[PDB]
Image 1: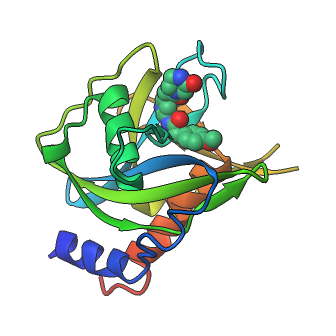
Image 2 (image 1 turned 90 degrees about the horizontal axis):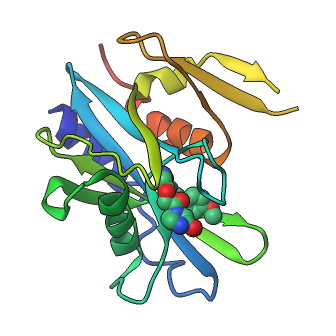
Length: 186
Ligand SMILES: COc1ccc(CC(=O)Nc2cncc(OCC(=O)N3CCNC(=O)C3)c2)cc1
């Protein structure tokens, strides 16, 4: 099946807990996969304009590890619940992808999660201005604008709204698309 095939692909790239004890400032992100209309999608947030870090930017759900978290995956799930109302029974964490090093002292660990079909986002407006889906296949043939660095523009055909996706967030989206969609029969 589509979902069994995605999980099987993802497991081959799982690094597990290999980098998780290193003494960094630690953040986790959740890369949330949603199946709709017979295709996989990623769920993104737009960050509230009130936030100190990166107001108004497109981001995956996530945030800084705190003492309550049993592990890095727990960080991602806690923050996702705060931001968009995703409950733990509504997500299956499938793997941990390559972590992202930034600023010399920070390590961001990305986890891919399969999202239940009955989840409906409840954006928390103190943290998130918007929540939206992009089909995974978009990231194989994105609409690129050079700003010099590459920016993706995605227009939602439901409403005509255009979102800009860039940086670590864009890079991770492409990685997930390659992992799941490469070399597939039609
Ligand atoms: C250091 O590089 C990273 C590491 C992790 C992340 C993921 C991330 O933050 N996702 C997120 C998505 N949408 C809305 C969000 O609002 C919550 C928020 O940003 N908070 C929580 C209240 N106070 C804060 O200081 C910050 C957060 C982004 C960048």
